[PDB]
Length: 145
Image 1 (spheres, rainbow, N blue to C red):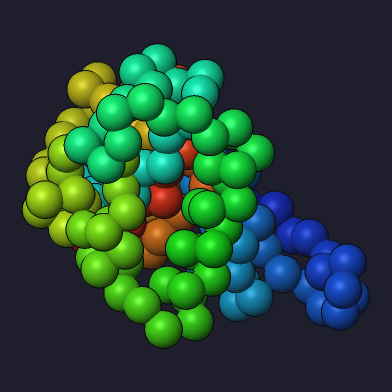
Image 2: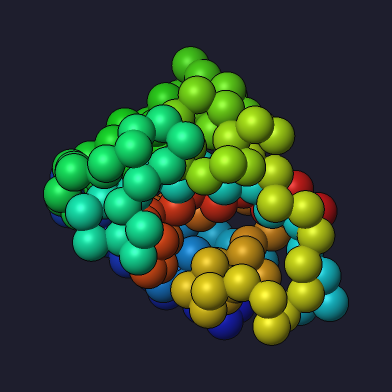
């Protein structure tokens, strides 16, 4: 397997899948580093976030557990094709990048919070992470270049 990936077994089906403990991504297909990447994100903040406040809500009171439930709902809508990542990042991200469909622009290593950085550089272009935890909250990250 490439670095970051491990073979796992579905608890519900018993089918093999693959999990990346860098990006928290999982996929059924067997998976077979750049100087800069470009990513978008959707952040859901919580009461333990470094700054519990955003453009959406002046005082963020949700628990980490409630923030992760929101994150998982958006992942399910995006992966089902019901909603596009851009649409949900514009509507629901607690980051001011929401105004740009979640886009952060391009960045090299050394610039972002480490968990966010490591997930971003470990994604393939077009790939979306699982829930990624930083001091700011929980992110879904889409690598766009």
